[PDB]
Length: 367
Length: 51
Length: 50
Image (cartoon, rainbow over all chains, first blue to last red; front, side, top):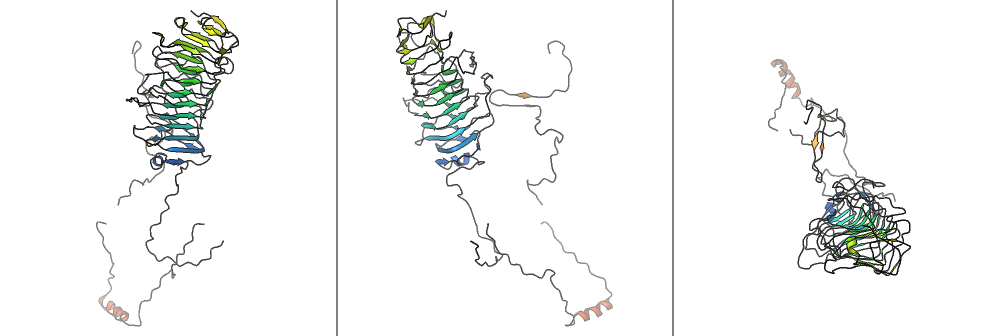
């Protein structure tokens, strides 16, 4: 404990080469450039309970990031954590246990959406397959939270099996966004809060099986010419599932976002379920709870008796005035059915009495 | 004798030394899509009508 | 180094005064003594970190 070994003096030699490399086995310290570490390893651990600062981290090879309770902040116009792939990757990406924050605090919910805010996301996957976002916390994003782009693929290779589970989204303007042709992936049990749009749906055939959206203005947006389409845009759209979710307090109660949204072409009035696309069909709709959540069924593909929108096993429950009301176009009265439902006394705009079983709600007409 | 690029025999700077360190020049940008213009225009000349 | 020199100042002593001073320093008892001002032996011993 005192080290009394004797020593001889140095003999004025040139000293031999002493090196102290391999100090991280696979980890990533704070204040270290992540682009040179993600290139070298396959699994990158992070320091437990650290405090990072990332901006435009380009990832080309699929790596796994165990966050261990890390905190990644950012500042600037770039996204965090840009994931660009090729078609030929056998490995997968798993981003796990990280709390992504934004360049905000109690975000500017009165500022309109524009081209300036479109690059304020935290994960932007270009064409990487089999990504996984598991147990994360995304706060205060002026743009999207994630955005899954996909370029033009061929040969019925629908694979791209993504998972977005167990996440917490607070204050993000747009939650899970997805580009066109981003088909057949799941996004469930993500607890939304204080978001303007929970799902900016462009790609179809998704599966949403447990998400909770409290105090959010919109949950399911699908129009023509939204934001966040990417290369290979609005094609083969809105075919997903939407089962057992929760969208309480979208119009009355504790909602804070405004109703206008300012799309790149026009402005529209948001609802808890806004849908307007003549070329796309409607998702399945089971087990969803709505307290004071509006629905706007404007246009789908009913052209040659090709689609019928059916609400099954859901709650409606909007009493005061027109809060939580369901709005349909008068040319779509024969195709919107509600079979199996519970409601307080909710305003139904342009829905026939024989098309709803059991007989609930107030039936009005909105010319 | 060459001293290399690590040589600076003075403190501060010799170019715009009075400027605030956060002040930009009159410049044009490229960020995202909108080429932002930021400028300061001392001279004022004419054009009472349409300029 | 492109160029280098070596400058020595020669004292202009008289040739008879020089020939008396040369023959006194050719003598074996008039050896020029010198000594280093430091007078020390360097011995650098390593201390490990900590």
